[PDB]
Image: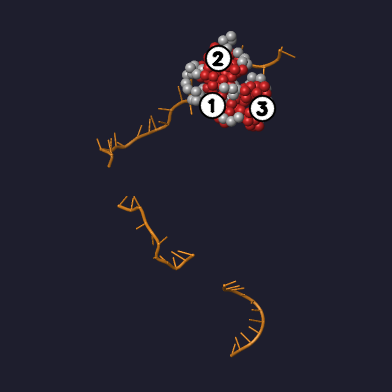
RNA sequence: ACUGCUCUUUAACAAUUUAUCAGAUCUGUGUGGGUGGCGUGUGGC
């Protein structure tokens, strides 16, 4: 509710970030200004704002040859969701493959484009090597 | 400590009923166009 789902409490921010292209600090500023969210540990809020570090590219660079399609064609919602889910394990190292990927599959159902989970799960099998000591 | 372990490689068609051989006008700036009603009073004839 609070710890894990925290991600999907602020993927909006990510989305808006990946659409606004402004200062991420002001991004979280306007986001917390939008509503008082209590299903998120503010430490995970700081993680989400830390999810700006350039390895973002690298994590899509992680799958850059491991892609079924192009990158920009992956919608901004999928872009942000997958980018933060890989920011868990590509630079932040929060949890193993099963836990974080169950998260990335369950907490994108109220945002996906009616089929997002199939492709994110089929391409996220790259999450197995990124933590090989699974 | 003590709600939280993969669901498995992206949108997912409406179009529809004789019938066919396709079957000259692109003007104006000539110009009229850019204080009274009523009442009362007075006086006159």
Q: Which residue is mark 3?
A: A37
- Tell me if residue A120 can be seen: no
Marks 2/1: CA distance? 20 Å
Q: Which sits earlier in the primary sequence, circle 1 or circle 3?
A: 3
Q: Which color scheme is applied? A: secondary structure
In the image shown, does A46 or A96 lie closer to the viewer?
A46
Which of the 4 quarters of the picture holds residue B23?
Answer: top left
Q: Is residue A97 left or right of residue A37?
A: left
Tell me the mark number nearer the camera, choosing from 3 and 2.
2
In the rendered image, the residue lying farthest to the top is A133
Q: Are marks 2 and 1 on the same chain?
A: yes
- Label at residue A76: 1
**Parent chain of label 2:** A
Q: Which sits earlier in the primary sequence, circle 3 or circle 2?
A: 3
Which quarter shows the C terminus of chain A? top right
Q: Which residue is mark 2?
A: A127
Q: Residue at x 51, y 17 (%)?
A: A63
Q: Residue at x 59, y 30 (%)?
A: A22
In the image shown, does A83 or A110 lie closer to the viewer?
A83
Marks 3 and 2: CB-CB under 8 Å? no
**Parent chain of label 3:** A
Secondary structure, mark 3, is loop
Local crowd size for mark 2, using a 10 Å CA cut-off: few (<14), some (14–19), many (≥20): many
Q: Residue at x 55, y 26 (%)?
A: A77
Marks 3/2: CA distance? 29 Å
- Tell me if residue A25 can be seen: yes
Q: Residue at x 66, y 27 (%)?
A: A37
């Amino acid at each position: 509710a609070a710890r894990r789902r925290a991600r999907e409490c602020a993927v909006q921010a990510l989305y808006s970030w990946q659409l606004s292209q402004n200062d991420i600090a002001d991004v979280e500023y306007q986001f917390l200004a939008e509503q008082d969210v209590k299903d998120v540990d503010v430490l995970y809020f700081r993680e989400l704002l830390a999810g700006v570090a350039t390895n973002t590219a690298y994590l899509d660079g992680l799958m850059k040859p491991y892609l079924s399609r192009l990158l920009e064609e992956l919608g901004q919602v999928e872009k942000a969701v997958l980018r933060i889910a890989l920011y868990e394990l590509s630079k932040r190292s929060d949890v193993p493959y099963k836990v974080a990927i169950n998260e990335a599959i369950e907490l994108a159902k109220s945002f996906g484009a009616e089929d997002s989970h199939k492709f994110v799960n089929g391409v996220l099998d790259k999450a197995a090597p990124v933590i090989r000591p699974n």
